[PDB]
Amino acid sequence: QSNRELVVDFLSYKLSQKGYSWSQFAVKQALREAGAFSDLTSQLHITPGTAYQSFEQVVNELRIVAFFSFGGALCVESVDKEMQVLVSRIAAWMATYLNDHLEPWIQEVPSQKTYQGSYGFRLGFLHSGTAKSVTCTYSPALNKMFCQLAKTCPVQLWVDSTPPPGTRVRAMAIYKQSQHMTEVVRRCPHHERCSDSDGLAPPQHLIRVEGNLRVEYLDDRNTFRHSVVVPYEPPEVGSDCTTIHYNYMCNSSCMGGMNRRPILTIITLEDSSGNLLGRNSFEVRVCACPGRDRRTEEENLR
Ligand SMILES: [Zn+2]
Image (cartoon, rainbow, N blue to C red; front, side, top):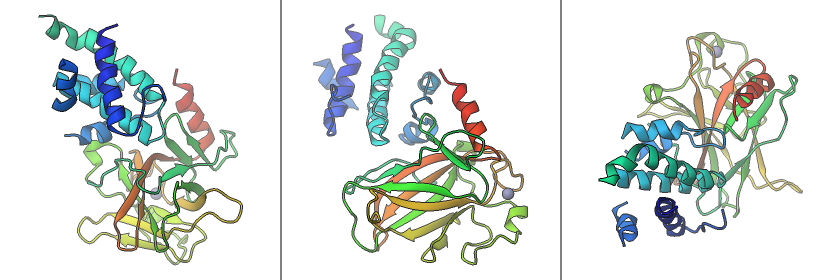
């Protein structure tokens, strides 16, 4: 009732420290200045369903200032990822955690960080359901894509402002887990050696693009990380978004490759000189029956 005020203060500050308002969604001011940041992005995966109470585990790791601050950045990151609703909860959680854990003490390696940038860069997805005949479906609640191997994956790009000609769109994959984040993601020997090649993609790259001769693939010479890039094109006549068709050419369960380890995909928006304009990411599971797998994860939620 007053402890809530201290949190909501800290957040509402951090809200207004950016271009955001509480309603849209002293020692107080001492903390407003006082405030391993990769923890906040990497180790957590904030998501409507996710962070159900994985927040508690994260804060248990660890200061009380860094706690109040931590929750501020979550809310920033929440609104960044278009997951504004969570700011409501993060405060509700933050209020509870203090009371339970901290209150007694008081009674006495590519970045996956989201940036919308100048152009207001967002990812859209078709809303395709979970019927067993779906090849490709996205869980907003899990911020997770479910698709079959070598099947079409529409990923929409959305922009506030049209970025100039020579802008490019690059996809890269990394492991969601910290213990695997340094290992480069690549295909498994079987799929690697398969008469499936489009004539363009390296045999070894997980992510391909479909129906685009202007595509281009990269093995970074210093990090050995695989990438695929295409030229950005503004929406076609009628549409309000750009649609790229990706393929995942190896399953999540494949031994010799991902070996049942979950991945993130990182879509970055670049200029011709390769300066970064924006970044967005989502989880991927490549499975046999995406519709079923999606439902099963979501059915587990509250
Ligand atoms: Zn494979």
